[PDB]
Length: 478
Image 1 (tube, rainbow, N blue to C red):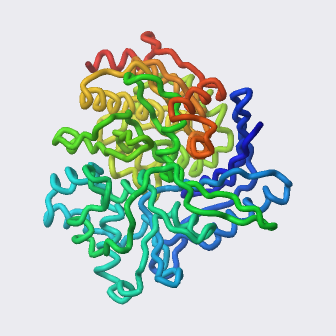
Image 2: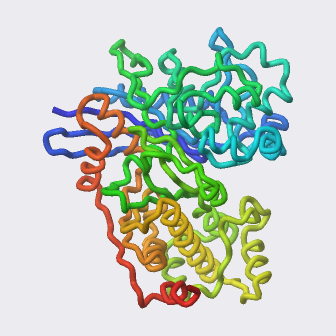
Image 3: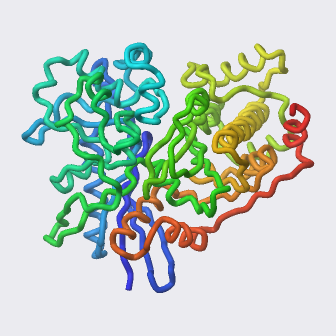
């Protein structure tokens, strides 16, 4: 009375083939890593690219490592980062290189689109924030610089659906990842004519975005048994939020990682000028529920520092950070200066000086700066979101790799004056599986899955502390 589901979770730095076991009886769900592999940007001669073919191998290796282990597979599901896509010709052959979002080809195009179509028109048609590397600008870039490829393009597939195509031979256009392109109209749930027109892309290159849950096709294991491949909320962040144990309208989530996200769920999107000024985005989620969110910096800051100072002990570091007072060193984590400087330590330090503050030079102080600044940014963003929807939040759910940092978790609670529930850490993978289980008819909906999660995953509550240094700080600057 059990079902085994495979989740293919791919990130910008790594990929994973996870196997989950759902025991309907006990209402229990367990994870288990089957195979890991590296992912990374490559520079194929002036171009920044993804080695899709190496990723296809690694996925197949793990799919196969499971079948060789005599384990029965009920369904497969792939989720990845968004925005990126792979072009195919009618013969099913790749057309050109799989250009990453981190390429420079789109420089200047975002600003051009706003001048030509209109900031508000683009925003009100798609409800998606303006990120310099959105699919829209990448497609415009594709047609403005590679005129030759255009006639050979028959299909454009978002990264998650491509790998699904390699496994099944069937094509798909998953809704949630689809909305990240800034090419989908918020009222029809279909590609926006006027935006595809500006991009230069062809509508025949895409098909009606279809909501998550459909069986894209089949994959055949070493023998011949057919394993169904399901379209899950392919955008990793949509999967992460699905698995966030939300309960109610007063709850918020913060997808904590290298890059982070903070938002809430809503029946309708926010496209007013307020939402526009605050850089808010209305991403597509499961059940037609929008993920009204805002892209936030994240731990990439600490990563670069742990890396530059050759720090191998994350703990001890957290321990040492705590001997230091807080809110002595404050920077703005969302400032462009932190996207990619040659020296992250020199940049934090420069920032602190520009604001007549003392300079954080030790490891502890650098970590102290990052953390206090993040919690403060988080608390500010949460405040933006409450002001947008019209009402405070009662709980903050932190999921992903970053929900493990208890020092950051207690700081967010103290800074937000809001209760924080951390977990689960495998948010993206869990959400992937959740949708699969809904398709296998094991669970009825997201809330049903979230309940499984709230009891399955060991969640951690962090209570706000009004006597905390960071709490005092917020209070007096307010």
